[PDB]
Amino acid sequence: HWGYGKHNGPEHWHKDFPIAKGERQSPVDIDTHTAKYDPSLKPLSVSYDQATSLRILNNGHSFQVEFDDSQDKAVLKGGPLDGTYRLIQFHFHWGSLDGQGSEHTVDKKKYAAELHLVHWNTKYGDFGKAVQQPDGLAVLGIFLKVGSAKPGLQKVVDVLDSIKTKGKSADFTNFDPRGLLPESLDYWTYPGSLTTPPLLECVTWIVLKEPISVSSEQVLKFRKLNFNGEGEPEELMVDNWRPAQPLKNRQIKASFK
Ligand SMILES: CCc1cc2c(cc1OS(N)(=O)=O)CC[C@@H]1[C@@H]2CC[C@]2(C)[C@@H](O)CC[C@@H]12
Ligand SMILES: [Zn+2]
Image 1 (spheres, rainbow, N blue to C red):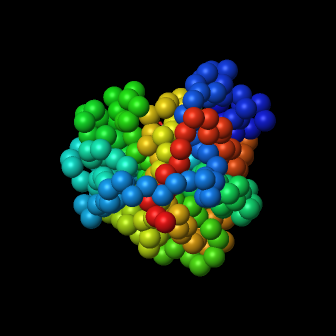
Image 2: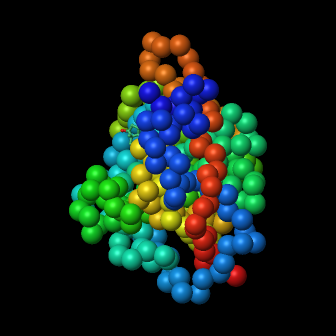
């Protein structure tokens, strides 16, 4: 029954999911001055040329674009990662206003939205086993700011009216997630968690420094989605972000000087 409202939002999650108050929770504020450049970080490799999207789904908390992960296609490796991680889905978090919506913050700055490209460590065979491991997932996080439109996002925006409500899905093939990436792959990285229940501490976070720009019209369409199912009172899907959590005993590393 978790969600993002007053009675079931982030401050309530710890009752059903005690790990909410754990030692490696996400998101976090990225203090850019305290993050240390790490020249030990191997180069970061995003190989999406063969990515094959299947479907887009309103899951009641966000919308997600799913990929066929049954073959070695669409892999993230290098950077802080050992081994190879396979793309399974992407989704977003966003606000009711352009001044909020991101989960991670940068020197307390909130972006209008945040994209999560979720990948699982192939050493664990599939996603459900990977999330039970401390190094099971790698999530590539990309900030969105409102400005120029992102042409590569438009195909996603245009299908949203077909999945307005919780539980609706639509075929969504041939979508190329390379169109959602900024020019630079400079990043911050730290060990953390899923940002929604069950809040499992299984994620290596890789957060790109360079945001992508999307237009006001594009994010406005995100905000027309509904948290509710069809035939239920309309509740706009907005502010589906968890706030920053305590850093505790963790160091954020930068790939750049
Ligand atoms: C693993 C990253 C992941 C996946 C999902 C969410 C959150 C997630 O963590 S995060 N934000 O990348 O750190 C929130 C909604 C989830 C979704 C995938 C699985 C679902 C559970 C759907 O079945 C229904 C709700 C969906
Ligand atoms: Zn997410």
